[PDB]
Image: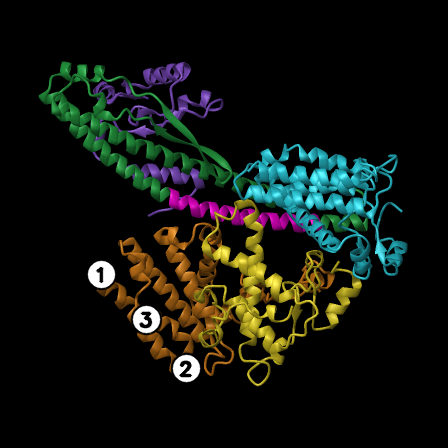
Chain colours: A purple, B orange, C cyan, D green, E yellow
Amino acid sequence: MAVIADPETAQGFRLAGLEGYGASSAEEAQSLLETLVERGGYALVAVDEALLPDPERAVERLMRGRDLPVLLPIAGLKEAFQGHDVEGYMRELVRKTIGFDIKL
Amino acid sequence: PGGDMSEPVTQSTLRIVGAFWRLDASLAFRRHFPAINWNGSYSLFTSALDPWYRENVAEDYPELRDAISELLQREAGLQEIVQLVGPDALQDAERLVIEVGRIIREDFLQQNAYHEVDAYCSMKKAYGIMKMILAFYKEAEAAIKRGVSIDEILQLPVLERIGRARYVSEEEFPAYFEEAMKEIQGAFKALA
Amino acid sequence: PGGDMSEPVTQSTLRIVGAFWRLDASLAFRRHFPAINWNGSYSLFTSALDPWYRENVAEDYPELRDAISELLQREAGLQEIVQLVGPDALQDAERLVIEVGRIIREDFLQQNAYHEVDAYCSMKKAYGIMKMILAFYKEAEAAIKRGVSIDEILQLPVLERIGRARYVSEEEFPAYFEEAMKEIQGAFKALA
Amino acid sequence: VSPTRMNLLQRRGQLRLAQKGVDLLKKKRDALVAEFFGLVREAMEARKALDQAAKEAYAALLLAQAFDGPEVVAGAALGVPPLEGVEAEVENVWGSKVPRLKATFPDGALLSPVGTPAYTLEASRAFRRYAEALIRVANTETRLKKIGEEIKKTTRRVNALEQVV
Amino acid sequence: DRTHPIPDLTGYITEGQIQLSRELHRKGIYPPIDPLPSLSRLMNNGVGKGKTREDHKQVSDQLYSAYANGVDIRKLVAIIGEDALTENDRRYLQFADAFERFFINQGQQNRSIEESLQIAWALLSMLPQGELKRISKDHIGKYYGQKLEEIWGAP
């Protein structure tokens, strides 16, 4: 539905039919997330990973009462043009899930 | 009756004996002999016997014994993770520790009573085996520090020489020990 | 004294009598009478009385009794997991077994000694009740194999008929049993 | 409690049942971890596919705004109605239920906007493929999170039993 | 209670015990002998190549291990469901059920040692060929592959 990223990425998401939004700091990103969930942000709400390292921090208030929204981090326009190390993100996920490093 | 150690006879016995060699059925189930559990067993004659070990075996014998005991303790400390996620999910150091412990268990603690030459072992042969194991562990850790893969270490040919050490005759042991010691340092440094 | 079943009189009696009917305090507290502990009771006359049951009650009475006992045993076995992880952690078949055990406990084993009709129950009435329960269990498990939710089965109206079949007089039971069997068949076969 | 022989036997039975339950929960944790590893592998593969789709979509974007003017691509974006409607089907994960996301699809080119130039057309198609990878990534992430939650619950239960009861 | 003085002393003097299980008896199985807690301390002397058959001990221990594994799996299948099991777990569950149904529940039959060994091999044939880790390849090659047509020969 709605994606929060840099304005250049927002233009592309509007081209794709998604409700793209422009943002460059955590405050307006959190405000947009709050107004989306308050107005009924439907399911997927993508947020630029370099903007909000963990989008769920603004969802902790509403995560208890709802399960519909799904938020995941993703690279922006300029961020994706450089190498993205998603494997470290997976390692962090596994370390949080189990409590030990699992790969070398 | 029942194997409980809280029974009064066992409690009274353990307060006056100097040693306790805990035989275990679990070790015998996996065909490990003479099946003395090293986690539960203990002895109180080490401190008094240390000077005799220094005089008649080697000056560094207590250090080798303590190193072997510490390696076994560290191997036993990791048993939770190797049971939860498996051995292949560990790092290089953890896998090296597990494999060193396995080599120790299969080549030093284990002994065949019915074997012609392996039935009896002197102090010199045990000291040589412990020194060989410790030297190989040091070389393997150095190779790991130099970026060598764990699988490459686990396929070296000197491990067979180490494994056959306990089946070597008592009088012919020193030459075998010297050759194995030379091969241990040759296998790592020459390959580079 | 004190409900302790290890008291010497109880042990002396237990080695002589051919039948043992142990009572439970928990069932009495729940006001669930006759409050006979099924797990703690037995009888040694079951095998010798089978020909009489075949001749005078029904040809397949022992099979129904064995099926009921097996179902009770399976429910008792599953109760160990139920008390550990809760009833909702089970699958559909285990939940069905638990519900069938509850139905057996509340509608067949239970008996009102102060009721003008439930006080006396002939062999044929109990045979009909257990036949109805077994048929319902068979149909329910068949429906479970067809993907029907367990919660849908528990609200089927024939459960009320099965529960109230205990209060039917000895005269109305022969037709009540036929009507209940037809209703049980219709609630599953015709619905599917 | 009242000290009597029957109570002692009952307590010993309770201890044996607790030990059996601890072992059973340990086996359940092992099975959950075994599933978790495969979920992690498939999530990594989905993430790599999503990254490739995102990179190619951005490459298709870079041609749209350069050869065609900003107003052309803006009008193309405004022409298409926004995509709305995500089907959140339920998925069973070891008793727990997780939403599985799939979105409605307007057939794409059938809803073409006034932005006729080909450089604009490619970006929207690449974006739709990118979102198709994104929904799969979200689904596998949700399944992995559910598996992790179950693993955490089982571990806490095992520790609580074997250290308290 | 196995800690009662009478069974405690009896086991402290004798060389094993045969344990009857109330669960098997209530499930309609006779004789309700439970292999898992049963034990014989002199069995290794009474079997071999010149007596009974050369595959007796390996078959016995393989049966013990397989039955224990199947019984243990049957507890987990209650909570995790059947579909979450691997193929080996389903094979073990079916083997345990068939073992309880055909091996232990012999009724009033008089099975010779050869018939019991044949039934045991037929039950083991349900498991995969490589799953019999406790038996030497010679006995497996000589006896594996028989289907279940033994208990039906004596209803």
Q: Quadrant of residue C42?
A: bottom right
* Location of residue B13 in the rendering, given as x and y in whole percent from the top left corner: 69, 65
Q: Which mark, residue B169?
A: 2
Circle 2: residue type = Ser
Circle 1: residue type = Ala
Foreground residue among D63 and E150: E150
Cα distance in 3D space between marks 3 and 2: 17 Å
In terms of sequence position, does the residue under pointer 1 or pointer 2 come before the other? Answer: 2
Circle 3: residue type = Met
Q: Residues within 10 Å of mark 3 (few under 14, many from 20)?
A: many
Name the residue: 77% across, 53% down.
C58
Q: Magenta stretch mostly in which secondary structure?
A: helix
Q: Which residue is mark 3?
A: B181
Please determine whether, in this image, residue B108 is positioned above or below residue A92. Answer: below
Disc 2 chain ID? B
Q: Are marks 3 and 1 in contact (CB under 8 Å)?
A: no
